[PDB]
Length: 57
Image 1: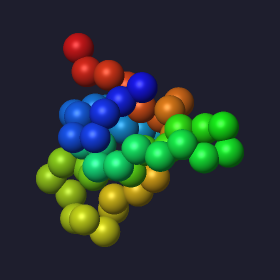
Image 2: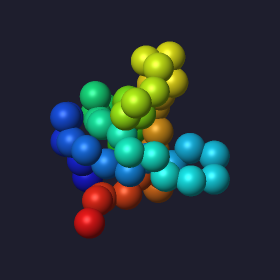
Image 3: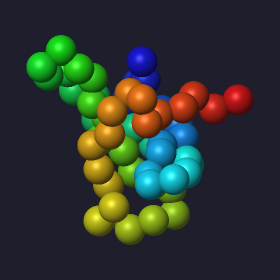
């Protein structure tokens, strides 16, 4: 699990991008994370699932 404001790696297409978690939600027995991709337009902000997130380090 991840927290609001946490720096994470987020998978988009084929690879992982530096990202920040903006919002956390739980619905239909699953966690979703609204992320912002660091150094990218706000327009790319999106909801992603747990299996597309990676902790740093």
